[PDB]
Amino acid sequence: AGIKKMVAPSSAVEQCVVSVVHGNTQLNGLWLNDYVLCPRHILGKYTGEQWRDALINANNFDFHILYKGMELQVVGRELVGALLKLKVSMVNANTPKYKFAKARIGDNFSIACAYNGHVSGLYTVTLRENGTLKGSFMSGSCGSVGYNVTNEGVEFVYMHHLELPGCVHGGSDLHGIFYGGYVDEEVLQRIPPAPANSRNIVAWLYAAVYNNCDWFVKYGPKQVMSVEDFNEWASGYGFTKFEYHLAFDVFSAATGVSVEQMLAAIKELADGWNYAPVLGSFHLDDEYSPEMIMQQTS
Amino acid sequence: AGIKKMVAPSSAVEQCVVSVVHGNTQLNGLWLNDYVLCPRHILGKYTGEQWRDALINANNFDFHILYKGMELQVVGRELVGALLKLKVSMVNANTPKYKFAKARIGDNFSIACAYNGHVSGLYTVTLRENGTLKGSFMSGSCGSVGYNVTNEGVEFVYMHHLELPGCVHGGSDLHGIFYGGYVDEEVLQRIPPAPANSRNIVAWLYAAVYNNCDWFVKKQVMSVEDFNEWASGYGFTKFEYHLAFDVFSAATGVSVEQMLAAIKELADGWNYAPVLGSFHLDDEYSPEMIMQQTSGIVL
Ligand SMILES: *[C@H](O)[C@H](C[C@@H]1CCNC1=O)NC(=O)[C@H](CC(C)C)NC(=O)OCc1ccccc1
Ligand SMILES: *[C@H](O)[C@H](C[C@@H]1CCNC1=O)NC(=O)[C@H](CC(C)C)NC(=O)OCc1ccccc1
Image (cartoon, rainbow over all chains, first blue to last red; front, top):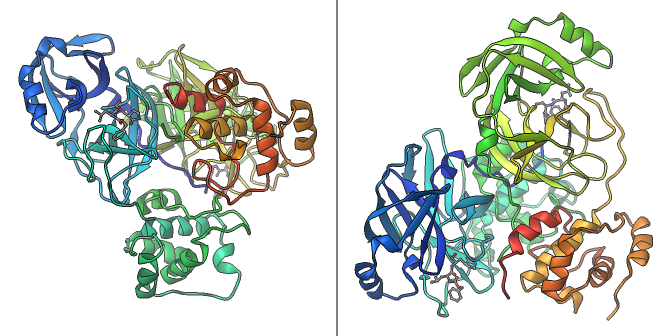
């Protein structure tokens, strides 16, 4: 029992994290095969077609790359979306089996938070409705990657670029595509809102029942709210339309609590509560994917 | 900016995690040098003096150990407090620089939660006043270790043994000493409740101020002496100094006494506005975990 934010083990990622320094810009890259990927603002702060011109005019010898104190010489440079791809003269002999994948809204993945080309800390994030994260990043952490680990190998899903006002973090996939409607420029940007993820909240409320925290359904006469009714309510109250997940078949069977009881709970609990904590909290938590809860309950 | 539960990188620990199976009992161990440590209940469910005799009567060949699917033959065995130390036929050539150290109350450390000798996920815990953790463990996860990564190398501080009432967890240090007043026996054990850690709450409120959330200090400061008297009757620990607070107070312009007054105001919860997303004081962040996440904040 117990419910925690589960990070994936980082050994395969650590063997790929490098520093990349150009001028006064210090950030991190990802070394796979014979190349390093890093955010294109390693070049400086540009917009639009200025990135291509900054690429043409840069010199490979001006990019200083280290892996654990060993220099990697840059022998080619190219832009890949919002990333620079720097070919280097040495193959990473510890390149893991890997794929590049896109995170889906509501998914968790793990951040290998790095400074000076060394991973300093790992943590879980959740991809929000507007393609942002609530992470923990300071100057020097750009190029930190987000990843998952499966039976097949590592999946790299994210590389960090920027912090929007309100501590809203933004980045790209490893093909250099930004995850939401923001760009890597220090100008004000209007971005769609981030409604609470109802699906994830249902997973967390099941987690609570698994852990004998069930006052919000076991006390008071049973209530249910239909999906249709819940969706119409949710659209006016800053929650996402409900989406089903196969985990809920397992959870509902094991707990005896239906999905419709959980939707009615969300509506009742949506302004918070003070009766008793739910998994330590007095507000609904949308940060856990159904996968993360299943891995800790069954 | 932002505040998250920060786990230490796991590469060094992963190269030490093994499965240990004895009969129907499946758990994990820690392979360092030419030995593996694992919980003694790999032997069965014994009590008190029976463990010594159960270890003496076991055969080395009845312990099956795998590292990443590779067999490690047990060639010796010894009881070390709550652990078995199983000598094996191969030295771990990836043994990191390490020490065994005791976590202190309020400390964070990272858990490498393992099943079948494979780390499935990591998370952070906080050593509570009564020597328990709020972790996440299922059957098969015993022998998972807690660790920190420091300048010197890895510090192994915890090995997992059991789940107590209330979804709380207990275990030992790597000398086999249990962290609180409990043992590895499946009988009801009464353990003293754990007050909220005031020191860590102070660190978390500083974290909020670093992140431009400071409504709760915006006078009436409270002295450490008055705070300690109030805390002793309200389920909070006495304040304890931590040298991170010299940095936090200077950077934020907010004194510890302001923060202690805030703890008293906020002790029953609030609903004015969130603090770092929360409506109750959070004691799960050590001052070291906050410092690591704020040291580069300019604003
Ligand atoms: C890269 O290391 C850094 C990460 C930031 C630093 C603070 N917290 C982060 O996540 N990224 C930047 O500094 C980034 C560089 C630009 C050229 C994209 N700029 C930034 O994040 O400034 C904050 C900001 C971004 C967009 C509009 C208004 C303010
Ligand atoms: C060892 O893997 C296991 C870890 C427990 C399993 C459930 N959650 C844990 O943390 N330890 C035990 O099973 C332990 C064995 C004794 C001989 C020490 N007994 C125990 O923890 O009893 C409580 C319990 C609660 C829920 C399921 C199984 C056991």
